[PDB]
Amino acid sequence: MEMDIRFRGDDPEAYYKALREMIRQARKFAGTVTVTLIIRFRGDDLEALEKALKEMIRQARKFAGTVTYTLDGNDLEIRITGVPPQVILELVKEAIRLAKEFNITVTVELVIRITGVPEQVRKELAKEAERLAKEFNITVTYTIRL
């Protein structure tokens, strides 16, 4: 009685707005939407990475959630939990922005943990996940439990 959705290496506005609408629909529908966000930064400019950490910590710590991280030399991992789903989309836009500003390499991943929803919702979101994967040519997967 649960559906997860996993997205990675996201594309420009057309995709973000579309995704947002799926995000929106899901929240409305009679269920619990638990979202988790992961980003990994890479680059030799360690000073840049340390600030990219600090901006995302401060912004995302203003939500009723928490933040964890690790630095495997020149690879910084960030795991954000507890954030409202309609904002999540915008924290994605901010972490891409930091990739450009500091001229560093960044990857992004969204985990949506939907609990107790209709099979009509599951099939539509599936079709929307099937659709977006193909139009934008990116990493898209999902899981359903019963």
Image: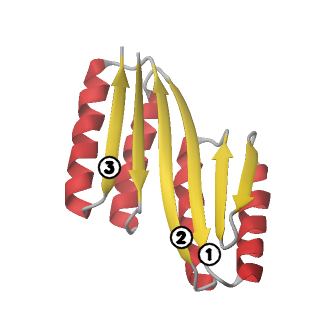
Check disc 3 and give the amino acid type.
Val
Q: Quadrant of residue 39?
A: bottom right
Q: Which residue does the numbered mark 1 point to in the structure image?
A: 98
The residue drawn where x is 32% and y is 49% is 140
Check disc 1 and give the amino acid type.
Leu
Q: Which residue does the numbered mark 2 point to in the structure image?
A: 106
Compared to residue 142, the image places residue 56 above or below, namely: below
Q: Nearer the viewer, residue 83 or 108?
A: 108
Q: Quadrant of residue 128?
A: top left
Which sits earlier in the primary sequence, circle 3 or circle 2? Answer: 2
Work out which quarter of the rendered image holds the N terminus and state it: top left
Discs 2, 1 touching: Cβ within 8 Å? yes
Q: Which residue does the numbered mark 3 point to in the structure image?
A: 140
Check disc 2 and give the amino acid type.
Val
The residue drawn where x is 41% and y is 44% is 6
Q: Residues within 10 Å of mark 1 (few under 14, many from 20)?
A: many
Indicate which label's residue lies in the foreground, 1 or 3. 3
Compared to residue 142, the image places residue 30 above or below, namely: above
The residue drawn where x is 49% and y is 48% is 110
Q: CA distance from mark 2 to mark 1?
A: 9 Å
Q: Whole-percent x and y of residue 97? A: 57, 75
Compared to residue 59, the image places residue 84 above or below, namely: above
Q: Whole-percent x and y of residue 53? A: 73, 66
